[PDB]
Amino acid sequence: EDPPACGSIVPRREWRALASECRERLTRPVRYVVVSHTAGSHCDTPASCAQQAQNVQSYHVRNLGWCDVGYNFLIGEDGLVYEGRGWNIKGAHAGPTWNPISIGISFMGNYMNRVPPPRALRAAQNLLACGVALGALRSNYEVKGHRDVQPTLSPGDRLYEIIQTWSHYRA
Amino acid sequence: EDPPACGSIVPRREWRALASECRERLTRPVRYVVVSHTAGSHCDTPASCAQQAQNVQSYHVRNLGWCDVGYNFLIGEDGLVYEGRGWNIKGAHAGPTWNPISIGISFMGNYMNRVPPPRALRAAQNLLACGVALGALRSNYEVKGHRDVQPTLSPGDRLYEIIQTWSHYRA
Amino acid sequence: EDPPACGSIVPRREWRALASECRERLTRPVRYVVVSHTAGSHCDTPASCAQQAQNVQSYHVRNLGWCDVGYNFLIGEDGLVYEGRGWNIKGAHAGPTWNPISIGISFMGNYMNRVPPPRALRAAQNLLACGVALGALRSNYEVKGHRDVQPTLSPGDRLYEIIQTWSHYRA
Amino acid sequence: EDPPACGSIVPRREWRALASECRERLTRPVRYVVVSHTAGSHCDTPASCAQQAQNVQSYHVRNLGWCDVGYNFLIGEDGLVYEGRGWNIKGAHAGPTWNPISIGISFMGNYMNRVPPPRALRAAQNLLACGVALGALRSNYEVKGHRDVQPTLSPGDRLYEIIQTWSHYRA
């Protein structure tokens, strides 16, 4: 089996992440990717973004009692991918119907009136292409916006427009 | 346009780079990758690193006279790769013996008494692997240290020690 | 609110199918029905027709990597109806435009030089009445030929001839 | 060596095509090429083919109400390449997933039990060289059978067996 030095993700340890108690796997290859946002403080530095991730995982563990941060991955306006649950474990990011079959990634911000910087869309887009290459994702994987699978605004109105334009995007 | 660009590289125009005037082309697949260190000021933020890449090109274009920034790629401590001359255009980073057979990648800063963060060591690593997929780099690519090819202290005592522990590092 | 009862359909489990990974839904009542043929070999027994169904689903999920068999239902020469993606989940049988607004039933076999046996027709025709009886289909639904909506020989010459004589068919 | 380097193609005006109303463009260099086969009747005189290609266009534009013939290029047995949607306009020949990332070439006629003549095959392979040479095709582009991305017999058993021998074919 083949494993291609792919991507650059800030590992848990690095953004100071807690230990995951999360133990439910996803069958490879996941067919869906659901893009969302934290609707909270946005960070533009590697340091402040590490903090932002820590803040999201915290609010998810200490307050929602989830086994870990909800998302499989997080994306910084700093232009970095943040390791959340990962490619192999189940996320708690979008309904029991969708969590067992999708990869949830969410830009750390509020994109109702703002747009994620170009560097962050590249992070995301690559993080994804990786997954395919790594075989975690199907090559014909489908990208959906949070609001396409739950009654919400996530991934924010502006980011949502942006992801419509993606080739792997399915309504 | 697809997705972006493996290695999530920051395009020239994104760091407000003056257009290159370079024409000499590299004969891919390239064999060498010469790691250096700008020798100048170090930045730790996307914004502060675009200003730094823009600064180096300056010295290379306005002052030294070259058609563009020396190195093919610059790596920021912001953990983001900045595209200089890219994968095809010959570099002006490691002399006339080496410039036509290697990718010159420079770390933004003086790595004599400190070392670049993992986030950049990561970014760099990816870049090379992304280079292989692109076919610009022959996968049995050897990685040399600036000081290994031309009398100089670059890429810094403490950076240089790291480079040697790289699987593809040779001398 | 009735109950008709007209589901003389072989359930996925009976023809032992892989689980559908498809989740996209058709709004009911659906207005159009598109008849296609598998173009494949023909089966004339619940035992083979069950095999056939496994195989068709197999060609779509394994070699094409599709969420699940393309059709919503499949007619066999065994005179039975096999449940494809059913009445509610949108199929992948007639392209981007008709898929979201039509049920696609498909005959298992190749009708360029054959007509499906009377019972295959009966199974089909009644299947629709059934779909109108539950309200899946609109009481005044229009029937198209696979080749009528997209370039193909489907549903085969002889069978095409027949469905044009059909009541609900439309130019 | 020298741009055109290639292409002996019958333009539209020549075979009297209708004006293309299509606008959705393709991104070069294109990575994939899907090989199809009209499956209708075959030709073999610049006159019978110029006629042939037109019937086909008519059909896709009239009966299915499209912008312009589905294919990008059609291959006659006269040994000529009839210009379809071209190298830059997205085709309508392989489903939502591959149309915007592939170029569709179709052999005029049905090749299930028969194979196109030496010349037919040269025109097409030549056409592909042409494509790479003009930068319309990624240099190490891949070739897919139609039945390899869509549920179909296209491009016939014999033609398929043949394209499965090519240097650019991928499972």
Image (tube, coloured by chain):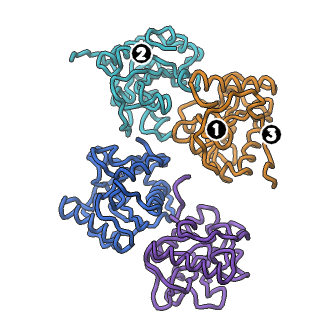
Chain colours: A blue, B purple, C cyan, D orange
Q: Residue C21 shows which numbered tag?
A: none
Which residue sits at x=29%, y=70%?
Answer: A17
Which residue sits at x=69%, y=36%?
Answer: D73
Q: Quadrant of the C terminus of chain D?
A: top right
- Disc 3: which residue: D8
Which residue sits at x=43%, y=42%?
Answer: A170
B44 relative to D148, above or below: below
Residue kind at label 2, given as amino acid type: Ala
Q: Residues within 10 Å of mark 3 (few under 14, many from 20)?
A: few
Q: CA distance from mark 2 to mark 3?
A: 49 Å
- Disc 1: which residue: D104
Residue kind at label 1, given as amino acid type: Gly
Tell how many labels: 3
Q: Chain of mark 1?
A: D
Q: Judging from the image, what secondary structure is the residue with disc 2 in?
A: helix
Q: Is residue A166 left or right of residue D130?
A: left
A63 relative to B148, above or below: above
- Of A37 and B126, nearer the camera is A37
- Badges 1 and 2: C-beta atoms under 8 Å apart? no
Rendered location of residue C62, percent (x, y): 48, 40
- Disc 2: which residue: C124
Residue B119 visible within the image: no
